[PDB]
Image (cartoon, coloured by chain):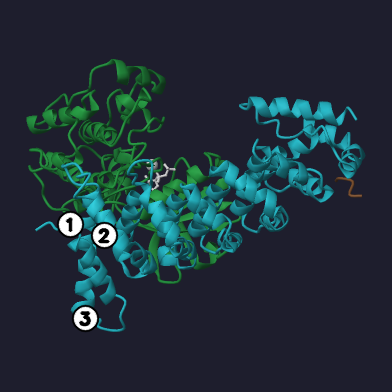
Chain colours: A cyan, B brown, C green
Amino acid sequence: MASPADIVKNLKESMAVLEKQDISDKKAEKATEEVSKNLVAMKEILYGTNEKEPQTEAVAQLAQELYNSGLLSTLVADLQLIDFEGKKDVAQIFNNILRRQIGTRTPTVEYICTQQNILFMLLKGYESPEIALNCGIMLRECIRHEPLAKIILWSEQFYDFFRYVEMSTFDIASDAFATFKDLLTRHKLLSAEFLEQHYDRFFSEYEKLLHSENYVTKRQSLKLLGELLLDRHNFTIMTKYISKPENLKLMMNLLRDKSRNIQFEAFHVFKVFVANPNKTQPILDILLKNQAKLIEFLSKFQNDRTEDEQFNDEKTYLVKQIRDL
Amino acid sequence: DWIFE
Amino acid sequence: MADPEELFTKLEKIGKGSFGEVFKGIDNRTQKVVAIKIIDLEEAEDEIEDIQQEITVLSQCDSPYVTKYYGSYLKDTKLWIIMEYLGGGSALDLLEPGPLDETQIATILREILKGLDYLHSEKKIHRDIKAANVLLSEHGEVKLADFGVAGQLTDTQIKRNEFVGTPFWMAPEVIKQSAYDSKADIWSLGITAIELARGEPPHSELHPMKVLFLIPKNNPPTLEGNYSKPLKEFVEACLNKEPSFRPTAKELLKHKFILRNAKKTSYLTELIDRYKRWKAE
Ligand SMILES: Nc1ncnc2c1ncn2[C@@H]1O[C@H](COP(=O)(O)OP(=O)(O)O)[C@@H](O)[C@H]1O
Ligand SMILES: [Mn+2]
């Protein structure tokens, strides 16, 4: 047959069946088969087997009818009820049209901007195991575009990430962290702003991560912190961070942590407290007090890491500094 | 261990 | 949280390679036999998210031609990848007592090309194709494993510019670190066919650092010996220094050799007995 947007009318209708009460025979199962076929039908409008995608009767009639039908929401709002390969296809569709530009405009980013709840449904997807990893894929594509990144970041619902990176399920919690890393690092200016303004409650929350029972959570959070402080755009956030004695004391204890990989990451944070020209009063108080015990520490610290140039140059820089007050 | 303090 | 050592009971070390070690084991909660792979994140330092990518890739597949993924658990620093258990051992294990006939060879390559098809169609590369990574079930079913180093290809970043695989099985372009896609997997399949035949790949005796200079400079390798012309020009389809001139996983399923003889599975349960006897010998 091959229709253009009777496919959109079909999907919409079948999903409606799949979301009503009982009927667990004949019709439930026949609706599930229909959603499958049409997500495929739809998926090949945009990609299209051994014949180019028609930059006309394909994308626009499909993109147009996706917006007017609100099918894009219905698929995220009901992602649950769809089958395995189904959720894989939904997410690939969602990603494709969200990437769609006509001109210098990305129409889907504009649509979502007015259908903001789609972003919030995706994010909230982390709390439902059967769909968490699919919502991560889709959410993370949204994040690629600054408007939407902004929507999630500035929402109060962003601090849900400090629960999500902490789940029970390792796969999911790891994916939560991926998104949460993507938010804070991709749109540099956006995230520099957010961090400057929300500093106090952000870092109060970030500090709980550095104390995690979960090894991955701790190691990765700590690794990220170092990336954030050392960034050029985050100059101001950095200065505030390295002025607080409670902060130095944590890093220095993390230098002496059970895990040598965590000690290593602690090093790249600790590194900047010392390289800092404009130190503050209790900064010096701890350094000079712990001088020499540090110069002794640094020399005999991760020497087995000689496949690494910079590291060994930074160590000789740090001892030079802790012997120069 | 460190001097804290 | 969620302690694996409580809700899984690990039994016989079933293998032990690059990342960590694999154990047979039981799912106390359901009583399913699973294979358990355990990686020490602390020692590892491949990277760390780069490690978690073997799970991502594997956890997206749902094919009978790929080892099912059941979950992962974290215990201090060791990560337990829980996946579907396969009894009959590697293709490479099964080649150990002695050679194999062109039916066995063909049916194996059939089963692998299914899977090689599942993977590529959704734009995934295995990159580590060899008899060692082709596990069998006690029923004699043939499934892809490791990856390990499987790449994902997005709609941007179509080709690939990385540095992976094992040296004898690598495709000229991968060694040269040029641009490559799923056609690299087809090369490696070629050399897998030779391995399944002559029991060992092109330049088995040479040094790794040699064959990384060899593979790109020299001509493609050929099936030399008493082997039917259906395959000699089959492997020649794959082993072609030009990628785009290599067949797809789809049409290689149509190729003359697979279809003689494409005998059903289970008819390989011979090879596993054949190996179970040879082992206790
Ligand atoms: N699901 C499984 N069923 C049976 N054996 C397995 C399974 N997974 C791994 N093994 C055993 O472990 C060996 C190597 O595993 P692999 O995944 O290649 O690890 P590595 O990447 O460390 O080499 C295989 O050849 C096989 O013998
Ligand atoms: Mn392997």
Locate residue A83 relative to residue A57 in the image: left or right. right
Image position of C152 with respect to A169: above or below: above
Residue C206, position as x, y percentages in the image: 35, 20
Question: Mark 2–mark 3 contact, CB under 8 Å?
Answer: no
> How packed is label 3: few (under 14 Cα within 10 Å), some, or many (20 or more)?
few
Locate residue A227 relative to residue C60 in the image: left or right. right
Q: How many marks?
A: 3
Q: Nearer the viewer, residue A197 or A131?
A: A197
Residue that badge 2 annotates: A65
- Specify the subunit that label 3 lies on: A
Question: Mark 1–mark 2 contact, CB under 8 Å?
Answer: yes
**Residue found at x 60% / y 47%:** A191
**Residue found at x 57% / y 60%:** A155
**Tag 2: amino acid:** Glu
Residue C182, position as x, y percentages in the image: 28, 37
Residue that badge 3 annotates: A25
| Quarter of the rendered image showing ligand 2 | top left
Residue that badge 1 annotates: A4
**Tag 1: amino acid:** Pro
Locate residue A28 relative to residue A227 in the image: left or right. left
Q: Nearer the viewer, residue C42 or C88?
A: C42
**Given this view, does label 2 or label 3 mark the residue nearer the observer?**
2
* Earlier-in-chain disc, 1 versus 2: 1
